[PDB]
Amino acid sequence: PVSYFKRDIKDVIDDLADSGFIKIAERQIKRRRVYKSIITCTAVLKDK
Amino acid sequence: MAEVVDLATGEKQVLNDIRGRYECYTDVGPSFQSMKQQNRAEILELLGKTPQGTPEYQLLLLQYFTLLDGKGVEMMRDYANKQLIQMGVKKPETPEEQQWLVEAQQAKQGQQDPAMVQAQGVLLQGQAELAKAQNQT
Amino acid sequence: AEILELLGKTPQGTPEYQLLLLQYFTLLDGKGVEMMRDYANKQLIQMGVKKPETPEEQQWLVEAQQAKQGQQDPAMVQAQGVLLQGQAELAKAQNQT
Amino acid sequence: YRTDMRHNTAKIAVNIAVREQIEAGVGAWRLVTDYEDQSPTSNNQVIR
């Protein structure tokens, strides 16, 4: 046993994940995320 | 058998896999079209830099094994395989491989080494015959 | 590379071959490399020099491995006993006299 | 050493330094430390 997963990435799933092999414990992690925003001189069309 | 290792995973629902990921560091090297391409050349590299010794021949067969479809390539690749398994090194992919080969394969070294013992028993029977000579005395 | 350096500067003698196998042993994944690296290993342990990492290595190999030199050297003694049995037969000749 | 010295940062810091060493006669780079939680050289730490 002992495998780890992004809290962020497994949102709506967890339910389906527990009814398969649920388990628990928690820990903090330096990830790094990127965000593509779109822009014209006038305003911003798509953010983050 | 009661032992095994090295199986793959599904990871059912969308977007999942352990966070013990990065096991691969990044280096560079000649660009290849595909994997089979790289393995092919990686063997050629291994040839030439190696004597006409034994390990050479395997590489060789390995080479034919890696070749992609053809009238030519198929037949030889097929021989190369047959040879390699019967070399005992291949360890069959098992689509059939073992059956046709591993049979007669296991049959020879067995036969001989095993026939030599059947007759080696006669080497002792010769001893037994000398014993008979003793019994005769 | 440290092994490649060792090759060339060494004759086609014995120590050469080990280096060689060692070389295949060190190679990283592939259809090609795996099979040969695997042979190279098998060979090396059965050479008795490897000293298995033991993920399984010993079992499949060290067995039949220990089996041959044993068999032979040990079979030669089983029959070497017959070399003395020949002596014993001559002794029988003496007993016959 | 070979681990946290693979990244591009290590290779670069030098070449710049050398480039500079050639033209002006000098050059340099530094070493620093901070935390990585995913794939740390060791002790949840790395050097760079």
Image: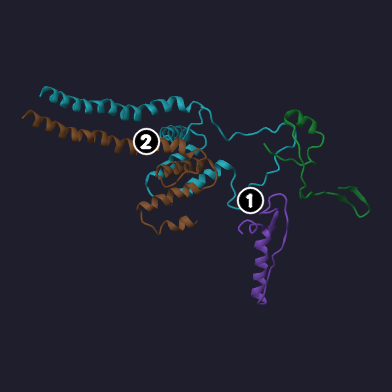
Chain colours: A green, B cyan, C brown, D purple
Q: State whether residue C5 appears in this view.
A: yes
* Farthest residue, direction front: C95
Dot 1: few (<14), some (14–19), or many (≥20) neighbours within 10 Å?
few
Residue A35 lies left or right of residue B31; in this view the side is right
- In the foreground, B120 or B27: B120
Q: Residues under labels 2 and 1: Cα distance?
A: 42 Å
Q: Is residue B84 above or below residue B100?
A: below
* Farthest residue, direction left: C97
Which residue corresponds to mark 1?
Answer: B25
* Quarter of the figure that contains the C terminus of chain C: top left
| Image x and y of residue C93, in percent | 9, 30
Q: Which kind of residue does numbered mark 2 sit on? A: Ala
- Residue drawn at (58%, 35%) of the image: B6
Which residue corresponds to mark 2?
Answer: C67
Query: What SS does tag 1 mark?
Result: loop
- Residue drawn at (48%, 41%) of the image: C38
Judging from the image, mark 1 belongs to the subunit labelled: B
Q: Which kind of residue does numbered mark 1 sit on? A: Tyr
Q: State whether residue B50 appears in this view.
A: no
Pointers 2 and 1 within a single chain: no
Q: Is residue B128 above or below residue D27?
A: above
| Image x and y of residue B125, in percent | 21, 25
- In the foreground, C20 or B65: C20
Q: Quadrant of residue B87?
A: top left
- Residue drawn at (45%, 32%) of the image: B78
Check contact, mark 2 vs mark 1: CB within 8 A: no
Residue B6 lies left or right of residue C79; in this view the side is right
